[PDB]
Amino acid sequence: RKCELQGLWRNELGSNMTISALDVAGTFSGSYQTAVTATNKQILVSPLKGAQQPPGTKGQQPTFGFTVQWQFADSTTVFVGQCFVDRRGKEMLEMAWLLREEVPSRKDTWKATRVGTNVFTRV
Amino acid sequence: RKCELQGLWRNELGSNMTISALDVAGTFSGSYQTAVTATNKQILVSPLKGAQQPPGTKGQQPTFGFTVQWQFADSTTVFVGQCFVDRRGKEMLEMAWLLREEVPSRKDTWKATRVGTNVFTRV
Amino acid sequence: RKCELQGLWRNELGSNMTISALDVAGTFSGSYQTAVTATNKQILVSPLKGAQQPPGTKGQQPTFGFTVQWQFADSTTVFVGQCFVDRRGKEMLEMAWLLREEVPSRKDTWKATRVGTNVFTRV
Amino acid sequence: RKCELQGLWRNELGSNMTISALDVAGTFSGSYQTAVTATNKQILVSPLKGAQQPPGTKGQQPTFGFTVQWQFADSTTVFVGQCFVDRRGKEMLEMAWLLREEVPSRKDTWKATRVGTNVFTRV
Ligand SMILES: O=C(O)CCCC[C@H]1[C@H]2NC(=O)N[C@H]2C[S@@]1=O
Ligand SMILES: O=C(O)CCCC[C@H]1[C@H]2NC(=O)N[C@H]2C[S@@]1=O
Ligand SMILES: O=C(O)CCCC[C@H]1[C@H]2NC(=O)N[C@H]2C[S@@]1=O
Ligand SMILES: O=C(O)CCCC[C@H]1[C@H]2NC(=O)N[C@H]2C[S@@]1=O
Image 1: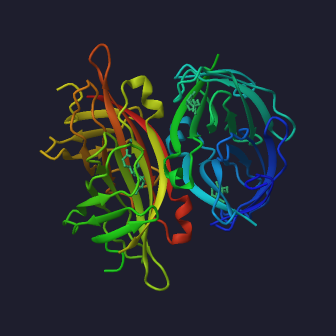
Image 2: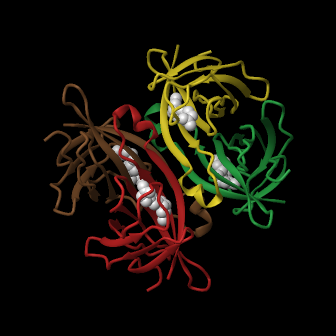
Image 3: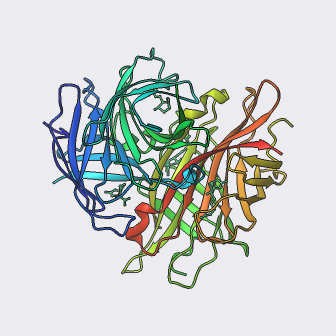
């Protein structure tokens, strides 16, 4: 089915992710291979956990989000988004994300969160 | 233990959330009772799914995130953050969030995502 | 003059903007013709006001930001970004933005702010 | 003059800012003394430039935004917000911000932008 989250996706940065089938409650797992890191550590495949809303009846794909638990950094990213299918059946996940760094003190919390967007296409 | 995610939390908006114990992989579930909605629907307790990094050894709490699958809206929120413990042992979760609305077309994606911050204290 | 902000730009949504010459302090003015709106109002050209950092000497273009005072809406947008010149000399402004709605009370501030990204190319 | 931007403000991080009188077009200037920095540089007073919407007639203060050109860093911040007067007449600016780092290449743009919120009270 078009825009099913399950499967292999790639974003404009060259990152890849695999999403599992959805459980009955719309929960899913997956793995994320980022192309880029703000750290200087070697990148390792990392697990993700999320949930997607059940589909409506208006020809629109439901919203979803997940958390990436990076295996090589102390940071955590969450992504939230919605899939779209164009005229030609090409699927795209439009996503926004927040990347949270682990900071030394509460006084540094103001600087801890970066934000961005990604677009994923089906591999 | 201080800053253990498991338990009952409340934010400045008056929202409440319960977080489960962490599984071995640092995955957790929970429920979220928001005080506020951008919709005009009646608020219903909603499930959450997330993951937390394992703790370091520097006296700092690890980062974490989760997804809220709202039971009364087509939207999805993700939250990402870090707990802090003050001089007096009062715990606070410092969080940033993105709220994603389900939009009718890809051309409306630009307007689909709101952003904010919350601070949770232990109930 | 590569990556000189002064001039005419268009982003991926079809929005156009004109930036005036920078004054000595790096402040500038301009106009912004958005292709899209979250309102049901007729879009009208709107003024912008901003500032850019002095160029450094390392071959990297300086960061800059601006505010757009929409003439057809009660909201305000801020854009912040940096210009890049590709291998062929083509200029792109990579920007992130926040769109702030005017809300009826303080309790409503939580839902007031949308976030996104745009890329502009020279017209 | 309740919620008149002109004047002196301090936020929860200890930052101070002075906003000049608004000109007829609602544009303004000012200075910003941040208490905190993501750099290891000595903080220096920095100029801001912004704009505010014309007051409506519904008893709600208009949205506004500004850019801060940090004098001690290569980054730029944009703030966007709205003033509120509480039951006792106390004014608070509820603001969200983006802090854009200058990055060495375009490929690095993804990590360039931090986001957060501040609340200002009249000094
Ligand atoms: O560097 C880190 O702290 C962990 C790796 C973060 C990779 C980021 C980057 N990769 C990607 O595919 N989209 C952006 C948003 S994700 O936080
Ligand atoms: O209105 C909706 O679309 C679903 C409910 C969203 C509640 C928001 C609001 N509640 C809260 O505790 N923090 C903020 C961020 S959450 O998206
Ligand atoms: O609808 C409104 O409230 C005012 C118009 C906002 C247009 C938005 C939209 N147009 C554009 O070029 N980029 C995005 C970010 S801007 O806030
Ligand atoms: O360190 C830098 O790059 C420049 C200074 C940035 C200070 C930040 C910090 N100060 C403040 O009052 N609110 C937050 C958001 S502002 O970007």
